[PDB]
Length: 212
View 1 (cartoon, rainbow, N blue to C red):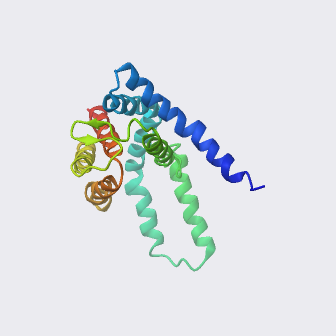
View 2: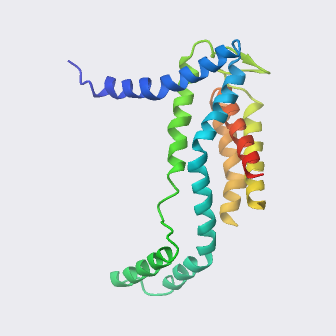
C-alpha cells in the first residue's frame, strides 16, 4: 500500500492546524449570526492577543540591538579592514561579538523566531478560508471573503506602510520596510482571497494601536 507519510503528515496539518482555525472562525461567526467578516476581525485580534507576550519580547530585544548597532558594526568595520585569510582572525572577531552580547545578556539568532510563527498561522488561516465552503462566496462590505479583490490588498499595503512609519517615529532597512514590504503585500494580496488581506489590515491596525 502507498506510504502513509503523505496522508498522515497532511492529516496532522488538517486536524491540528487547519481545523482549529476553521472551527474558531465559524464558532464566532455563528455567535454573530453568520457574520464571517466580523469573525475574521475578532479572530485576528484574538490571535494578536496570544502573540502579544512573544511580540513584546521581540520588540524589547530589537531595542537592545539598537544600542549595540554602533558597537558591533564597528567591530565588523574593523575586521573588514583586517586580513580574513586566517581562520584565527575570524575567531577573535567571534570572541569580541560574543563578549558584547554577554555584557548585556543579549542573544543573536533569537527574536527571529516570531518571524517564523506568523507563517503557519497565516497558512492555517489561508486553508481555513479555502476549505470552509460557507466563507467562499460570503460577501463582506464590497468583497467576497473567499474571492480575490482589487481594492483591499492596497489597503493592506497602505496600513503596512503606516504601521512601519509610526514604529520608526516611536537607512537601508528602513527603505526595505517602508517600500519593499508594502509592495510584496499588495502583490500577494491580489493573488490571495480577500480574507487574507482583511486579516492583514486588522493585524496592522492592531499593531498601530499597540504602539500608541
